């Protein structure tokens, strides 16, 4: 009846960027390459965050919602956001602006816990989005930029843990 902190994370970003692959790497320690692109789902896991046992809830969104009101309701439920793009697809980086605005409209707080996540860092030779331009956007938004690979696990725990650290600090 002792209650753990429950950190509600939402994955956002355009299609194919790695939302599900990041989620499933974090949850199950597997790189999953064919996860149904239209499927949204939630995941929960106990994690030890800076020595404190907590629960993380991850909503892996898929952009499928029947109404804007439904999408906004999901976003309103979230406490922090991983805003993912693929470093190999410039258009997915451009699309992060829309997710940022959607989140800000619902959460009404420019300091909402939020990381800009450039995924597919193992595909450096296919990079379309420079580190510099992504860092500059993160600086404009006052968020951290982290590059990840769901394939190699690089920075996967970091993005989820660092987002939980922002939720913990900012929603106190
Ligand atoms: N090389 C590489 N491929 C990735 C990575 N993350 C996702 N993928 C691939 O990109 C595709 C889309 O990933 P997915 O997680 O389903 O994208 P979502 O639509 O954002 O959920 C799949 O074929 C994945 O295997 C990554 O970090 N590196
Ligand atoms: Ca997905």
Image (cartoon, grey):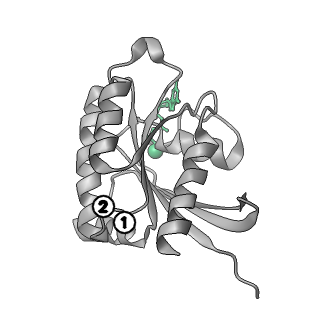
Residue depicted at 57% across the width and 34% down the height: 150
Mark 2 surroundings within 10 Å by alpha-carbon count, few (fewer than 14), some (14 through 19), many (20 or more): many
On the picture, is 65 further left or further right than 166?
Answer: left
Front disc: 2 or 1: 2
Q: Quadrant of residue 4?
A: bottom right
Q: Position of residue 143 (x, y in %)?
A: 38, 49
Give the residue at mark 1.
75
On the picture, is 57 further left or further right than 101?
Answer: right
- Closest to the observer, 89 or 161: 161
Q: Quadrant of residue 140?
A: top left
Residue depicted at 76% across the width and 85% down the height: 2
Question: SS class of the residue under badge 2?
Answer: helix
Mark 1 surroundings within 10 Å by alpha-carbon count, few (fewer than 14), some (14 through 19), many (20 or more): many
Q: Position of residue 128 (x, y in %)?
A: 32, 20
Label 2 beta carbon less than 8 Å to ligand 1: no
153 to 50, vertically: above or below: above
On the picture, is 98 further left or further right than 82?
Answer: left
Q: Position of residue 31 (x, y in %)?
A: 63, 34
Residues at circles 2 and 1 in contact by the CB criterion of under 8 Å: yes
Residue 95 seen in render: yes
Q: Quadrant of the N terminus?
A: bottom right
- Closest to the observer, 24 or 39: 24
Give the residue at mark 2.
103
Question: SS class of the residue under badge 1?
Answer: helix
Return the residue found at the far top: 125
Residue depicted at 47% across the width and 69% down the height: 170
- Closest to the observer, 58 or 113: 113
């Amino acid at each position: 009846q002792n209650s753990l902190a429950l950190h509600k994370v939402i994955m956002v970003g355009s299609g194919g960027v790695g939302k599900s692959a990041l989620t499933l790497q974090f949850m199950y320690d597997e790189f999953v390459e064919d996860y149904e692109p239209t499927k949204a789902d939630s995941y929960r896991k106990k994690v030890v965050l800076d020595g404190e046992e907590v629960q993380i809830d991850i909503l892996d969104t898929a952009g499928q919602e029947d109404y804007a009101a439904i999408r906004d309701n999901y976003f309103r439920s979230g406490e922090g956001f991983l805003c993912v793009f693929s470093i190999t697809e410039m258009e997915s980086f451009a699309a992060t602006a829309d997710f940022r605005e959607q989140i800000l409209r619902v959460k009404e707080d420019e300091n909402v816990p939020f990381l800009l996540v450039g995924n597919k860092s193992d595909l450096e030779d296919k990079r379309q989005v420079s580190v510099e331009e992504a860092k500059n956007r993160a600086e404009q938004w006052n968020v951290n930029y982290v590059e990840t690979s769901a394939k190699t696990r690089a920075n996967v725990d970091k993005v989820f843990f660092d987002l939980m650290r922002e939720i913990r600090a900012r929603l106190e």
